[PDB]
Image (cartoon, coloured by chain):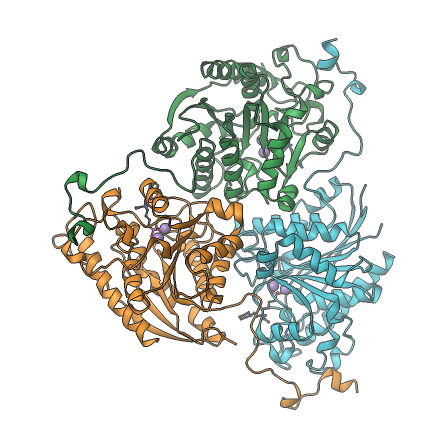
Chain colours: A green, B orange, C cyan
Amino acid sequence: KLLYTSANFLGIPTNRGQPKIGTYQGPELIRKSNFFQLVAEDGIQLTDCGDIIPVELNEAEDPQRFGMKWSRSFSLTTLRIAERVEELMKQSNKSTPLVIVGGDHSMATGTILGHAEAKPDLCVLWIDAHGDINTPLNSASGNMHGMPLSFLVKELQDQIPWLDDFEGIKPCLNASNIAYIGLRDLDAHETHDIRKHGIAYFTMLDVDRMGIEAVIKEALLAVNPRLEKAIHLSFDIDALDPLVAPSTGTAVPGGLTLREGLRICEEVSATGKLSVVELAELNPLLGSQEDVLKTQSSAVHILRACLGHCRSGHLPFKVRNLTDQGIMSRAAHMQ
Amino acid sequence: KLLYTSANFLGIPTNRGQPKIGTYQGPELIRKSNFFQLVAEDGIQLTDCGDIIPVELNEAEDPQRFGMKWSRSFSLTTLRIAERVEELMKQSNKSTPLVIVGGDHSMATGTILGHAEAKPDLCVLWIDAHGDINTPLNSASGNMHGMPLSFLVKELQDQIPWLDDFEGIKPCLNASNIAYIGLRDLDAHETHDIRKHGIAYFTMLDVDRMGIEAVIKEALLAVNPRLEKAIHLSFDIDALDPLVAPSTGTAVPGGLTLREGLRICEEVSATGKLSVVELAELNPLLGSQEDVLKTQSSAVHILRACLGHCRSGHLPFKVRNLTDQGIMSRAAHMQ
Amino acid sequence: KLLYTSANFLGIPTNRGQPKIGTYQGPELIRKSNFFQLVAEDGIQLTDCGDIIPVELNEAEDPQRFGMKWSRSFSLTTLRIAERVEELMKQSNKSTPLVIVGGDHSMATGTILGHAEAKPDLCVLWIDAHGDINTPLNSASGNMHGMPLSFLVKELQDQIPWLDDFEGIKPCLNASNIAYIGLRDLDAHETHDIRKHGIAYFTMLDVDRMGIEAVIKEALLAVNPRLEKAIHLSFDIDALDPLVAPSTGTAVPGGLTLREGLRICEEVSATGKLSVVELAELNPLLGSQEDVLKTQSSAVHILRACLGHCRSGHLPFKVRNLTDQGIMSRAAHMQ
Ligand SMILES: N[C@](CCCC[B-](O)(O)O)(CCN1CCCCC1)C(=O)O
Ligand SMILES: N[C@](CCCC[B-](O)(O)O)(CCN1CCCCC1)C(=O)O
Ligand SMILES: N[C@](CCCC[B-](O)(O)O)(CCN1CCCCC1)C(=O)O
Ligand SMILES: [Mn+2]
Ligand SMILES: [Mn+2]
Ligand SMILES: [Mn+2]
Ligand SMILES: [Mn+2]
Ligand SMILES: [Mn+2]
Ligand SMILES: [Mn+2]
């Protein structure tokens, strides 16, 4: 009756991928919610595997290199994440999805690296207002959370500066293994690289013209045609409209409705191939108390959909009967 | 020019169907609005028939029975509502719609009972995030507003515990006479009963995949194929997204847009078969002042659509002419 | 690579078309934003042409005439606007769009008058919750911002009272040159005139049933079939849902989503025929600080779309290369 009967939960409180303090509280925002209770109510055994501890160096240890901010904290954290995800995914070999809560999106380099170590032929569905595929010299901001895919994509490696501490970060993705949904604020050089190397992408313009149902279908068609590959679903909460997810660092108006977001996750879940889902860029320190509650709520509904929650309802495990308790029913009484 | 030239208005301030104080202020929230003025401006004669006084017993008189909270207050209130609705609907036999403002949704047992007494072959369109069809032993909450349909549906009576004071509450609905729109938070046993007895239902997943236009059509097709039956439209305000109706007790993210809600009401109205519309679960004591204003506004637009308001405009009753006032026009002056 | 490489920007702080103080701050709300910076980042040369100074008479000089409030301030302002727009549009003869920020919508009589002087065969796309086509004796409010089209439409001139100071305001539009999108709160006499004279209109009901893609297509088909005519896009910010544009004087629930608004502007822009776009009814003195920020944001995204911003991204003018800086890439290092 369930596609996934077990799941693992991992927190990754990354906060050195971008300058706004608070993404480190992301995992706790979800733990404080009713997520676990709701998942159990659906019959799923969810194991909290704790948090990864990011490496956070001081300024002296981690100066700017090629404009990148905290790049050694990044490289060390990436390797620590990858090791943990790899070992979690290998104990998993009905499959057992890994649910990851961030943390800023710089964590994705590590999670995908480790995931691909366990499952080399995976595909990536990237749900985001942003491309997150800036190579270091093209990044105006120097924020690592805008670069995580660039280190992973083989076709881009002539645009990545060599750093010794980045050697263990091996490019494990082909451009043909990635599909974007939700884009609406690409940098020019991202647009260039995406089009040049033929990365499948469906922006909010595409969602408007095609509808989310067709977009989801085409995205899966592009990178997982016959559902042969494990899916890495990388969900940036800022893919959703700021009206439903205001508490995040780089919000952009005109996003996915919660319903559109749910449809993406419902379809990905229903493939039976959801291997890892990560939810990035929750920041409970941004916005009002009600803003945080809305963002939390949206996140929980999204993550539930990923694990197979159905808005059309679930059947009970044991159907209750009235006579079993020795109780007279109205139907019984009338006869 | 008008499908309905007259209408009746009834308040039912039920608040013993659920524990949050404030649904009793629902009718006043609408009376305080510009609803009446706007309805008159469309040429409709709307008569305020006052409020039904719910029976509210004290704890000693109304202890828990079969887990139900305030079940004798419920049974007595149900009978009082039914008597009033029946007499209102029988004076009505262009038909004259009855507009009912709640009050929590437990009132629906009474309104439908009385309605069916006047019009036995009616159908029910239930617009709600919830099923409201829990039988008493399956209800974790014991809140009557989550059970009103269960006492009315004939196929469910082997699951209703017999109570003497419930005898006058006769099941008057076949499962085939009900269609849901907007569901997104069903209890497992509700899901079971709905599927088992073939109740037509269109959840938010269905709305996403089909679109609201097709959903409305299919819902009417399922329970009123040739528009032969009077329609009881039971509209829970929490069917709408919390962004447009935050002031309600059990809000669930990812609801109908106001526009989707308007389309439901516009189509139901246009059948010429709208016999009763009830609007449930307004709670002006929940949320901020602006939250209440939004919910009020959404409710007024919804109720106006039910009575035939057209967003594409109405024609004037008397067309004004310039020369009638003895005034020189620009066209006149240029000649 | 760009449809429009240059554009002009004009502020018109009209505030005598309606009684709520604050629309005069509209132009500054946009100047304070990052609009100019973002437009430049797309490669467009935008020239700020300053503000038009409206004529604002005192009460003694400008008493009510035919129920109209501030009608001489209106007639004088209209002529001053028209002169300025005409001279701006004639210096413009890749064309150079004129972007106008209001100001209440009464400015439209002046902007269209001047525009048509430069381009007599123009068409008008009116994006609004309201018709703004009340003739003076039918207007209950007397607010000029609800009448600007009535003075321009030739077919309506037998319903316009003659005033000497209105002589220079010559009707320059045929009813067949106008198409509405977004209507949802028409006055009865507006509905009458619109239907009587066959003005193309697509209300929110039409948007719901047809979808915005079809609506845009049909609107352009109705008034600009072969893209032969210059387009005057008159965008009332209250066309958008109050959830995304709360800071405006006459907000009506159930409006266009920001995305739907963007699609309108994206398609109009892509015709290559966008000649003038005006954005009306911004009022930074209404609503909360966050309300103003949302409205500002929505306005900037809308105006950017008009000038050709693409949500699917732009290509860089110069593609950056790694070796040009004398830097070793990862690809280089591995060989
Ligand atoms: N691409 C940006 C944003 C990165 C956000 C990372 B995410 O998706 O985890 O929140 C810069 C975006 N860009 C900035 C200026 C104007 C256009 C968009 C960057 O800093 O590289
Ligand atoms: N079905 C619920 C909600 C009833 C709401 C009545 B309405 O539609 O008038 O507002 C309980 C819902 N349920 C609770 C736990 C998790 C799943 C949903 C119940 O209490 O029976
Ligand atoms: N049509 C109205 C609104 C004008 C708004 C001008 B805009 O689009 O620049 O904001 C009156 C609307 N009308 C009022 C009563 C009920 C129905 C709608 C008027 O005052 O003429
Ligand atoms: Mn992002
Ligand atoms: Mn991201
Ligand atoms: Mn409900
Ligand atoms: Mn209900
Ligand atoms: Mn308007
Ligand atoms: Mn207007």
Q: Quadrant of residue B187?
A: top left
Left or right? Give the position of A122 relative to C48.
left
Left or right? Give the position of B229 relative to C35.
left
Image vertical order of residue A72 relative to residue B104, above or below: above
In the image, A221 versus C71, the foreground residue is: A221
Q: Residue furthest front?
A: A335
Left or right? Give the position of A213 relative to B85.
right
In the image, B319 versus A23, the foreground residue is: B319
> Residue at horizontal 43%, vertical 55%?
B222
Q: Quadrant of ligand 3?
A: bottom right
Question: Where does the image place residue C179, in percent across and percent down from the top left?
Answer: 69, 64
Is residue A58 among what the camera can see?
Answer: no
Image vertical order of residue B57 relative to residue A209, above or below: below
Q: Residue furthest top?
A: C335
Question: Where does the image place residue B136, in percent across and percent down from the top left?
Answer: 23, 47
Question: Where does the image place residue A103, in percent across and percent down from the top left?
Answer: 50, 27
Is residue B168 among what the camera can see?
Answer: yes
Image vertical order of residue B150 relative to residue A316, above or below: below
The number of numbered discs placed on residues in the rendered structure image is: 0
> Residue at horizontal 70%, vertical 69%?
C55
Q: Quadrant of residue A218?
A: top right
Q: Quadrant of the C terminus of chain B?
A: bottom right
> Residue at horizontal 70%, vertical 49%?
C266
Question: Where does the image place residue C59, in percent across and percent down from the top left?
Answer: 62, 76
> Residue at horizontal 67%, vertical 25%?
A176
In the image, C283 versus B285, the foreground residue is: B285
